Length: 287
Length: 285
Ligand SMILES: Nc1ncnc2c1ncn2[C@@H]1O[C@H](COP(=O)(O)OP(=O)(O)O)[C@@H](O)[C@H]1O
Ligand SMILES: Nc1ncnc2c1ncn2[C@@H]1O[C@H](COP(=O)(O)OP(=O)(O)O)[C@@H](O)[C@H]1O
Ligand SMILES: [Mg+2]
Ligand SMILES: [Mg+2]
Image (cartoon, rainbow over all chains, first blue to last red; front, side, top):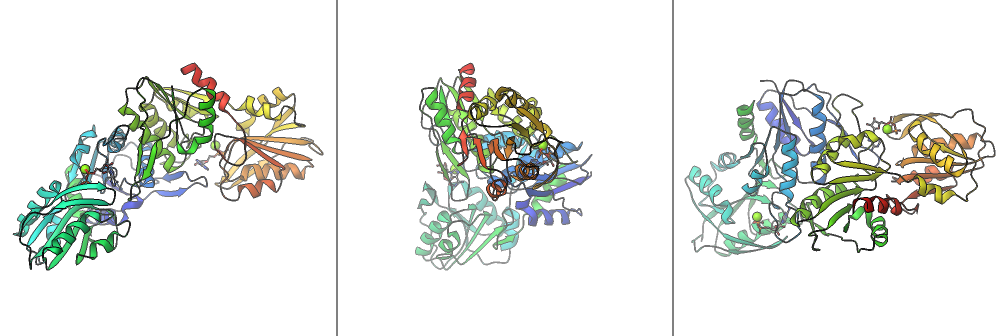
């Protein structure tokens, strides 16, 4: 049952929490950039005979290179298995072609990762279609219980999804909190703009928890937050699994919301909700 | 045929397209707000032999190549052929220590999974060709370097290391000149040690040729030792001129002129390899 938890640069915080829970020490590569900007890494730890769990996100160019080179480096050891855990899975928003001649980015990248591993897992992937681009079992873990635990003793009247894709998540979270829920219809206009239709639910004087998978520009949370505030909401909590927080996102959100709490899949000052338990449960099931 | 020009290779790709009597294709390209890469090919690639021209050494170059390999799947093409004038990660072609990646191996496996052929110019070590599932050709800049220097007054062609000896033996012979090589030991990313053979270069004009200039450490050290030995003039050439910060200065302190190819575009790209690449393409279609 020997396991090694590899912590890539993007995921030191979550990887450390996972390793601690599992009573093991995180393995980090010796790593640097050559002068020409190529990536170097090395695993001095003897990975022979162990189930290997590589923890790293896959959205930035550097994250991808670190994952790919890690997948080569560990071939130097006769490992028992190689299991990719990408807490935030990059390119999950480009899961099909929207115009002729576009890449299906999550397809080619998933095919690559699955060619070099025995399993892949992520937390709350943007669209499940991508899971079906993998030749190995690609598991979609869920932050639901961690979010419930954070809000167990927080006063909330409704849990709200900003889109129809998030209906199941919020039905589950509200169920577990003994609260009501509804979802908003969303249409994305461009990288930074969305349009919404909010159902005729009376939220006057009500405390709301909005939950989504990703916060990038904050356009989605900002729009839902603003429209709900217009409707008289008294307090709005915002949570998302993956907090990227680019392009003045924090300000856009807090213009109409009160607090932001995301998980540690992407490490930021808002990472108050750890998904370590969910990832450990998965690891124990494999190891 | 369709010639696709990735961002790293616009100049060489244009010269290639011109020679092959076609107009180059460039993707619409942008970064999403979260830094993810977007690209799109609007030109109908259906039924054509596709030649993707782009280097493969920086993170973005690799991502542009991988995403292009997905994007062109939207068209029913006749063939897909990668031409990476400078092939990234060719210096990590084996494991020097336990637990290192064979970077050139996994990347080559990836590229050869989505193409019918790969080519590069003067790969750093030929072992990497064997990592490919498909025909992987190694093109050569030798004749283009010879053409450039054919009427230049040179006494010796010099290789800074054992690896570049075959190249300089070929270039010198073609130029009717003598040659020798220096033995080199790399100390770290920026430092090498060399032993120059007992060759009389006092008042001699020298052409140093290597495959890659990165930091310029290798050229600087060789140039300096040869200058100490009385060399009167030193030309520096390389196939792939990366010239990372400081390299230009380090080299010009001991050398008189730098001339590299257009595999990597810079102000020193005076020697083009478009002919060699076009010759290769014509064999493919
Ligand atoms: N990382 C990204 N950031 C923003 N938009 C992206 C990203 N990747 C792909 N897209 C684009 O998002 C659009 C699809 O979004 P859509 O499914 O309409 O809304 P949602 O954002 O709810 O998934 C497509 O035009 C696609 O190219
Ligand atoms: N892009 C790169 N830049 C610098 N050094 C690299 C690069 N890729 C690999 N290396 C390292 O170069 C070393 C091998 O160099 P070596 O073959 O001894 O000398 P050289 O290649 O400079 O003639 C190995 O330690 C390898 O890790
Ligand atoms: Mg979508
Ligand atoms: Mg070498």
